[PDB]
Length: 392
Ligand SMILES: C[C@@](Cc1c[nH]c2ccccc12)(NC(=O)Nc1ccc([N+](=O)[O-])cc1)C(=O)NCC1(c2ccccn2)CCCCC1
Image (cartoon, rainbow, N blue to C red; front, side):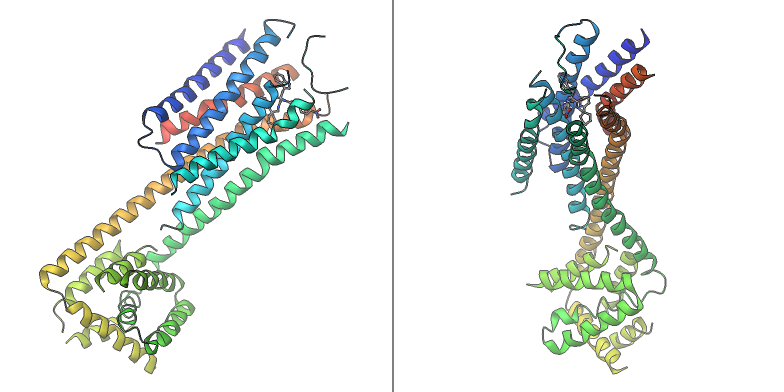
């Protein structure tokens, strides 16, 4: 009575959720990216699992008589789901860290995971009255169940956790910076102008001491040094001056106060060409230091070769790009936490199923635990789209 009602309710909820998910993907394929395609693959896998797990239970409940392909399809479904979760976590890591023909590559990766799943579900058809009983009559069931646990639960979630460790680390470093580049500034936002004279004067007589200055800053300020290194790398790449300056400032302002103080310093330098006094004041916070101040003054002079109207457009573009990059990072972390919710619900719902299936290899509230575990397995697919609906 209670069990059939709750089972039908959750089955309907999950089927409707996955159908709505895939239908939304079909309708709005015009807005579909790596994450959208991967959650589409997840929805397809979950829906196939539902459609192949309903009939066996229905036949075993409302009948007593009923084998080589259904378990293959079910294992294919679970493999597709979990490996697409892994690929989605990898996408989140590669999109959050590195950007602090692609879509076709994601599509062929989806094809690849489908194919490797249907190839890894081949052994199922080997060993699967009128009751389709795969379990024959010691080591084969346990070994197969452990293999399914490893291939389908353990290493995929392990990869997801590994690639979220370096999504937490990146944000922790970005938080350490800003706080460090705002407490005792003018070591930053001045060396950031001694990292542009190096770009301007390409002679090795500048970079030879610029590398040493970066090493000293790292010995004295880690976040400042990493921001300066990213700034100079971007500036050198985009130089081949204004583009180099924009790239350097953008890379530096990536781990709120820094943009404001830098805009103020640029405005002050716009009318200094007594610039030496301002450079000395900025660098107040050792002949190598004098040479670095000279290079910073060179970069300030280069910036001075810009009209009042021209510099305003430059600072406006720079601050707009800073804001856009911050917003994109926030959106990326929001999608990362949504996928983390997906992984959490998946583990909470599929750990009981996996542990019970590993235990059942021994036996090749028992009924109530079995039915609640199956309802939980379906509830995973129930709450994936519910999580995406509520969180987004
Ligand atoms: C799909 C089926 C049952 C099945 C076997 N026939 C059928 C005919 C019709 C409908 C269903 C079946 N498949 C095997 O159990 N296959 C197997 C059995 C014994 C041995 N052995 O003894 O070595 C080796 C392999 C199975 O419960 N998956 C195990 C899992 C699962 C549970 C619920 C829903 C989906 N997925 C899939 C992920 C790992 C743990 C749970």
